[PDB]
Length: 415
Ligand SMILES: OC[C@@H]1O[C@@H](OC[C@@H]2O[C@@H](OC[C@@H]3O[C@@H](OC[C@@H]4O[C@@H](OC[C@@H]5O[C@@H](OC[C@@H]6O[C@@H](O)[C@H](O)[C@H]6O)[C@H](O)[C@H]5O)[C@H](O)[C@H]4O)[C@H](O)[C@H]3O)[C@H](O)[C@H]2O)[C@H](O)[C@H]1O
Ligand SMILES: [Ca+2]
Image 1 (tube, rainbow, N blue to C red):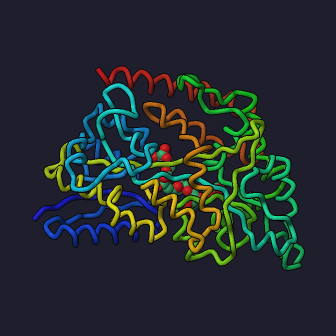
Image 2: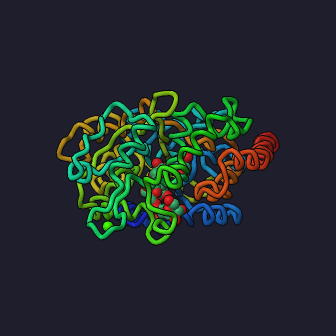
Image 3: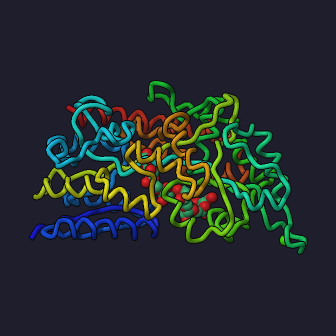
């Protein structure tokens, strides 16, 4: 008799996996029916924004940790503390503390207090390499613990860039990194960030930021260890990685099902190359599962969120379907140690979570518009038409004005 709407996003392999686990939920709870609204990752934010603007909020939905404070102030998210505490067996202490705490808010700051959502996952973004390619080229394998320096990374990438089938044309490249998701590590490992320590001042004009951004663009334009602009336009580098054309490409746990289906070469995980700090860096992603403050069935809505986030049966089904690593720390640890589950160095994912992964800058700000502005006009830098130095000087005041406005919202909306 009960009906819940569950809104979320995913790549095709993720949509299938969560639809399957929702069906499992419905088998376990024959009185609850779940109506699914699913979208591509790229369409999700617009669709969810529209639902919230209309105050037509799905019972259960994915949301961005950077929106937690805004969602609490606007009464979007139900406080689920008591339903979680009263639930049968569920103990959120087996779950990554880093994950759980992103969705706690005590009235003033994130990380403590009442629960306003549950972690979908933690998403450490690792660096993968094509071991088949390395071994066919006679190049010594990357070390699983010691990061390449930037110079060493470029060196090995040049060695991997070649005409393998002998038709006179390059057909294999060292890498082909997407700035949207892989610039952060180079920036962070070079001792820079988009914003300052206090999270109130834009710092993209830092010489260390500029160096990292120029190095990134230079992979394509100067060192030439990527497909050309035209070649990437013909077929994007994610697809070229899948077809075995690239030495290096990032790997998230959400990728594993798709990679199981499409990747026919051997690959493994390594630390990201390290800039001036000598320490590798990358991001640890997360999404929240929240419950509408306006839901007519809070108990069943939280049961669904718990099933996806924390229930050993729901969790086991998601991990088996290769779209995430276990939310339970002990289970993740035994998972990482199981050699029959590839890649071999799965442990790298845990090392990112525990040691050298960071949050996206927008997780600290009231909205992310200031950061979206940086990326909106970035492509001329990436294609070598504008220097990194010239762009960040132009972008910084635009970003700062947006950040200042986000801060003023934090103040006004929280009266
Ligand atoms: O190179 C130029 C570009 O290439 C062409 O576009 C090709 C792109 O490739 C395809 O995308 C491949 C995927 O992209 C990377 O994954 C990035 C995103 O992760 C997935 O979501 C997982 C989810 O996110 C994690 O949380 C991250 C953040 O943390 C919070 O702060 C915030 O809420 C989150 O956003 C969670 O832990 C986890 O559950 C998304 O699906 C994906 O977008 C990986 O390399 C691949 O999976 C795709 O076809 C194109 O985008 C174009 O020409 C040019 O743009
Ligand atoms: Ca060739």
